[PDB]
Image (cartoon, rainbow over all chains, first blue to last red; front, side, top):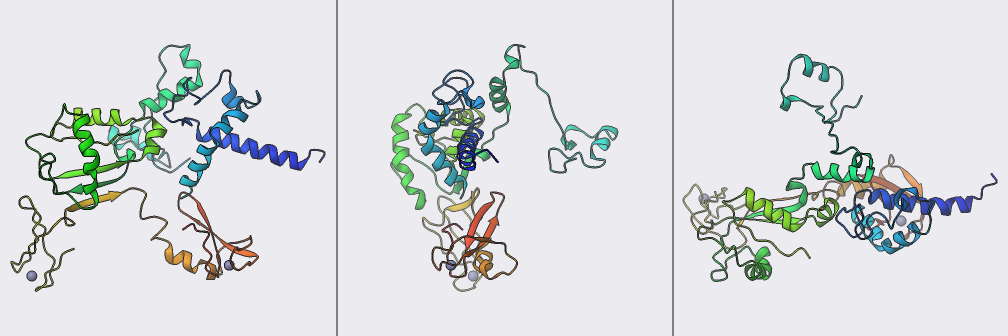
Length: 79
Length: 152
Length: 105
Ligand SMILES: [Zn+2]
Ligand SMILES: [Zn+2]
């Protein structure tokens, strides 16, 4: 109970958004065409930032880079 | 154990396949285990997942969201006569005619045509470009003649 | 579908030679221009979520057995809405007895 719910919820909403983003882009690339080795920003900006989620501020930038892509694909799927 | 297809291991299905010596086509739970070449690159998950997608079978049907069979031929831009809804295709077929002058419409085009649209999201998903589709089709199908739009 | 103007019978297509010419059992021909050239077609992931459930969606707010949720209706401001799940895509639709349809469906 000591844990703050409003902090838990806002962390989960970012955790859910980032997990769903990377789950959707498990093979897909935000710029399209797999290429999850190094190309563009499909996989990493160095290190293990794409799954480890605790290196911080790499997911905060990359997910914000392609937030529009995430919004447009979710509604296309939900149709 | 699951019942859905591809994993029909329910009841006696698998034991009969072994004991009754059913052929490859009769197998409802067939599987393979492929080892990535080289042992050091075999340890990487990201390299593993991409090779798995590459070896998977992608056919035309999953790259298409609608196709139409039309009763029309092509004699370049001199005779016209097309389906009304798809008559607008000559706006890119003329682009194709000059962008690809190496393979002009043959002298034996039959009075039939299939017009197909592509699901770009699937192309984006599995990284099949328009170049790879056209090249593979023409190599596999030599009694057909190919027109395509521009994917960019 | 072509029906004979005199016999009211279904006419074969008979693609001969550079055009489409319908023929009846009575020998009449009517031919065909432009819009008759569609021989066959197939559209994938279409014909689903529009024509299969239209009646069901329309009647859903009146079905006693449909599940309902606590959510304000934008139109009539009823405190409850009827929740609908259709397809292998699991599309959630909220409908109300006032005709509000969530613009989805
Ligand atoms: Zn008749
Ligand atoms: Zn209402």
